[PDB]
Length: 301
Length: 306
Ligand SMILES: O=C1C[C@@H](C(=O)NCCc2csc3ccccc23)c2ccc(F)cc2N1
Ligand SMILES: O=C1C[C@@H](C(=O)NCCc2csc3ccccc23)c2ccc(F)cc2N1
Ligand code: NA
Ligand code: NA
Ligand code: NA
Image 1: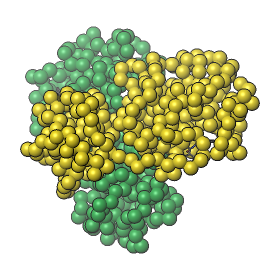
Image 2: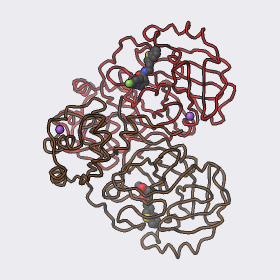
Image 3: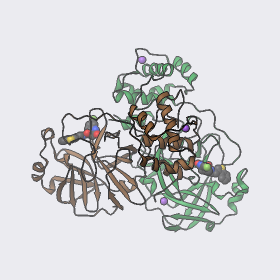
Image 4: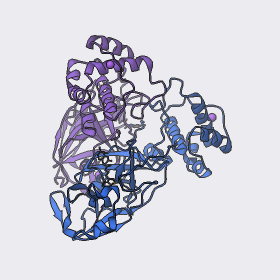
């Protein structure tokens, strides 16, 4: 038993991290087969911060302008192309440590592990959720761009995030591995701001089910609710709407614990009304929204 | 910016995990050089588990009674011996992925990364602190015994924990890699309980420094305190004593943020007496005690390990 914020083991990703240099700019890239993926903004100069013309900047570069280092070894860049906001550098060596992998684009509320990296070298690993406002609440310094987010549900690594930038509120924005930004953000230093963030309701419910599976019962109650009346209350606390999809997804945790979804919804209503009154749930004094239904089942049963 | 609970990258340890089977028991072992380390309780049956004679159980076993699998390969066990509560299985092949490593024993309040494993396969990684009562608040299911805890200091892995059991309250107990238990526990099925725990004061201060570095400053105040006066209040709240060594270790964060340790202690005093009054620190409504001073400096300065 026990319940922890838990990341995937990072070894399969660690063997794919390389350092990418263009001019005076160094950041991280992701070496899979014979391609290195990194943020296209690596090619930008101080001049080009606000309105880079990436097509124009790229055509001006040759292969030998890109220095890629894997450990102590330089790789030879033999091609370059851009896909949306990621740069793809063809290199003359396939990565012998390439794992089984795929690229997936995720939806808000999904969780993943981040391998934070500097100068092509792993620094640490933590867990994040894609926020409803399409930011992530990461831990990233200067040098971290090109760090990736991933899941590993069997032996296949699913890459779902590449890090591009920090917004003024200290939260983070980035792309899928096809270079499409999550949310309305762009890889320019023009003023942009995250929308107001909301709580991931389906994940909170999942975490309440985790608490019950781990023997915590104190917050339950004899009430139920309609889905609509739940949503009307929840929105007033800046909670995302709970949809029928979400109710369906909670079905297995509902059946394992004997507590119907709308019954647990009423428990959440009460917690929002009353707070915790000196108590904790799974060691937390706030409601946790960065565990999905899938996470709870995986870690518990 | 940002501050997260962050584990060490686990790859160097992933390449050392194997599966160990004895009879109907399967659990995890750690393969380094030509030895596989695992909990000695692997040799026990249900009858034995109440009052095991490990010496006696072991002498009855042959090498071929231990099935060790590294991926889909069987290793050949060519020797077996016990050191405290860990079993050492000599095998005929050195682990080609053996990293630079050492065995260290940690002190309560020190943190480490746990690589949770099942059937010799790593499943997850998280950060833990050794509690003052010598338990860890882990997440472990049946199959997890032999999972290990570690730090990385450079390119050197320091192994500091092996998982042996869950106590009735749902917290966890284990040994160093020399087989000595952390805390007053034994590897048998009998009544055992965690002592009452305390809060790791130096780590809370470290986390308050992390908060300030990340722009969270509401709890700061004009006041300072003495080490003695702080310790009288801390003891009253089931906080560990703060020593001069702790003050010294916080010196770097004190100088970087402009907030002396005893000045931050006055913030902590007020929080204990008054609570947080609806507010949060780094998104938490309770004081976090599972980041050391070293952890905060590492994460706020971006140290790496290729
Ligand atoms: O997560 C990070 C990384 C990195 C960053 O935010 N952004 C990368 C730059 C960038 C975005 S659009 C565009 C167009 C041209 C050239 C550069 C860019 C950073 C720097 C300083 C600091 F204090 C914190 C962080 N945090
Ligand atoms: O952390 C865990 C692992 C594992 C566990 O604690 N095994 C302990 C076995 C053991 C300890 S001493 C001794 C002497 C002889 C024979 C067995 C033993 C477990 C099983 C089921 C469950 F629901 C939870 C957990 N939690
Ligand atoms: Na690397
Ligand atoms: Na209810
Ligand atoms: Na003060």
